[PDB]
Amino acid sequence: RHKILHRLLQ
Amino acid sequence: RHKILHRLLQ
Amino acid sequence: HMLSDEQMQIINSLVEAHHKTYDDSYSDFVRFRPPVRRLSMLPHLADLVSYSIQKVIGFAKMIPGFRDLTAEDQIALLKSSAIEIIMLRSNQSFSLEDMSWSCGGPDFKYCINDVTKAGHTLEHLEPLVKFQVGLKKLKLHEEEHVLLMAICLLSPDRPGVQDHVRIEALQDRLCDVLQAYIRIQHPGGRLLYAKMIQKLADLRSLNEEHSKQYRSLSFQPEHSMQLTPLVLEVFGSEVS
Amino acid sequence: HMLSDEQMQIINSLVEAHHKTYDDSYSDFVRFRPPVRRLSMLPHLADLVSYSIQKVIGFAKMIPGFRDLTAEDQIALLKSSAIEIIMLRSNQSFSLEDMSWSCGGPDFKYCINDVTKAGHTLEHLEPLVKFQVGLKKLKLHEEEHVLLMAICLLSPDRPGVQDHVRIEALQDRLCDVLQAYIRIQHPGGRLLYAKMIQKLADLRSLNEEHSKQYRSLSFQPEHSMQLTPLVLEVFGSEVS
Ligand SMILES: C=C1/C(=C\C=C2/CCC[C@]3(C)[C@@H]([C@H](C)CCCC(C)(C)O)CC[C@@H]23)C[C@@H](O)C[C@@H]1O
Ligand SMILES: C=C1/C(=C\C=C2/CCC[C@]3(C)[C@@H]([C@H](C)CCCC(C)(C)O)CC[C@@H]23)C[C@@H](O)C[C@@H]1O
Image (cartoon, rainbow over all chains, first blue to last red; front, side):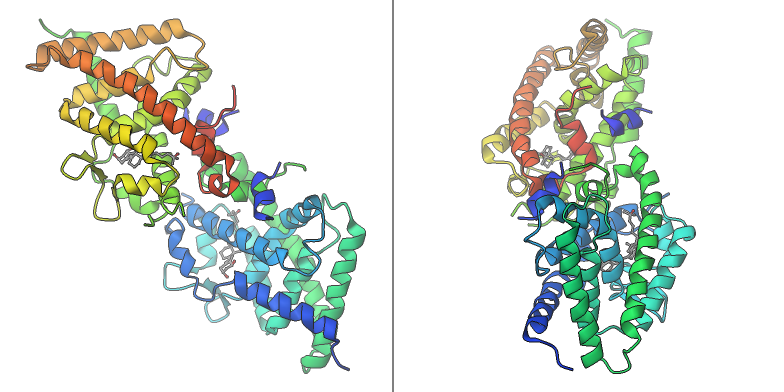
């Protein structure tokens, strides 16, 4: 689900 | 699935 | 009035297992992400805990009867008690003089404050220190400290446990060893055993409190990313 | 014969974005798990790559038009090109004198051998070094180096991409800027642009070769555990 990626993409 | 745990449990 | 030949064999094993998996020099700590003194200590402490988990696994595997369990049960026991075994084993580095775990120099000397910079409040850190002090004050023999870890690990009342009949049997077998060792080899220990069991109850509470602070960390991706794969898996709620 | 007002604005942004996300001192490297010289370099290099991924994300977000894309497309582009952007950006630390990335002292000086102790064979490491040498020999202007990274990132031909119409438009808009900058601001660069595009093709090949070595690492839990959550997620094959 790319939880970290979503997060880092503000 | 605990891939690392299985592994470390030989 | 004398320890049996079987009771002393399981002691030898447990004490050796702990020597194989616990370094009094703490020389591996240099390989962890350096400590920093928001949430600056999270990376170092995550590495410390991850490392310790591997050690606890190595120790567990050498606990008499553990390897004879199902991979599932072994996992259910390790996942549920990992943090408690870590809290127990750290007492060996804890120091009453300064109320902190002293693993070498200012770098690897962990005070209550350091852990607050790793996502934990004093609301949880207080009882843990109090626990360490009470545990240290018990001045456990190495045999007892080790036996306690193995009895903690083989606790029947854990989420996910399937064969809670064999587990309890292994644990009972261990408790007998402990109660006999204290009675025979530890003067003035007539009350000790009971106090050690109460500590196990304390650990349940500390465990509960840690898992709540950890849940918040694991839910914040910016913080969870600082953890290790092992930590995430072992402290995670995936079901096997 | 002159760069437009819009073309120079996007350059200013890209060059600033790179300054905000690339440290020439490499001072953050001390916070990574120390290098060790089997697979001893995996922890340091995993931290290096993880750190770099965060930097690449920060840079990407400042690429003109990137933030206007769907979270999905942004992810599909980052997941697919992350390694290529890392390979590009590292050229800035690569040195021809010693054929290695020099980030400070013996510790952070990475030679081809170091990477072999992180799960990669010379079967893949050879082309990468050759790539760095060819790239360095191009003596790119900062404007060109930066433009190249942004054009790489906004490549249309990536698995998972949905709106490959807008992406290609943004990339074309960028290529024009690059071809115009070289023509106008870079003497003897009449052939340069074409050579830079060929490098992008090289990156596809390097990417393909890395993802294969990485697949083996990620499949061996004893090695995968040494990676970071970000690396596992970004280089993982989960589908959004
Ligand atoms: C571990 C060991 C040691 C210390 C344990 C500590 C000291 C620092 C703070 C710790 C790590 C506590 C933290 C609340 C745990 C944080 C968990 C996390 C941040 C990941 O949610 C639990 C045990 C504590 C050192 C040595 O005794 C080895 C032993 O093995
Ligand atoms: C990154 C940067 C740097 C070096 C990149 C290197 C040098 C060491 C070996 C690396 C890291 C290559 C490895 C094959 C990547 C390993 C990937 C993994 C082991 C996780 O599967 C790719 C890029 C190479 C340093 C600096 O330029 C910042 C830049 O940002």
